[PDB]
Length: 32
Image (cartoon, rainbow, N blue to C red; front, side, top):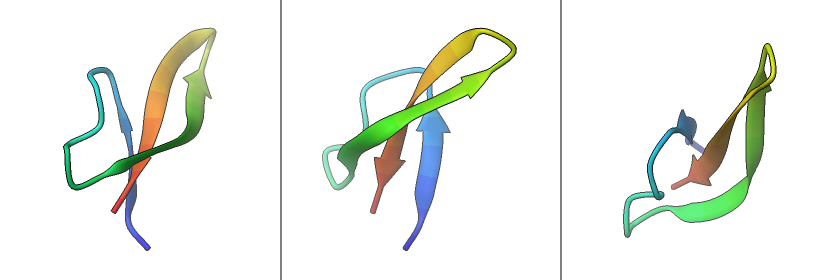
């Protein structure tokens, strides 16, 4: 499905599914 790396909390229609990491900086992975 469709997953996004987000700096905020996942949309309520999305689930926290892991983290993204770029160059030491972390994001939530949020999948619909």
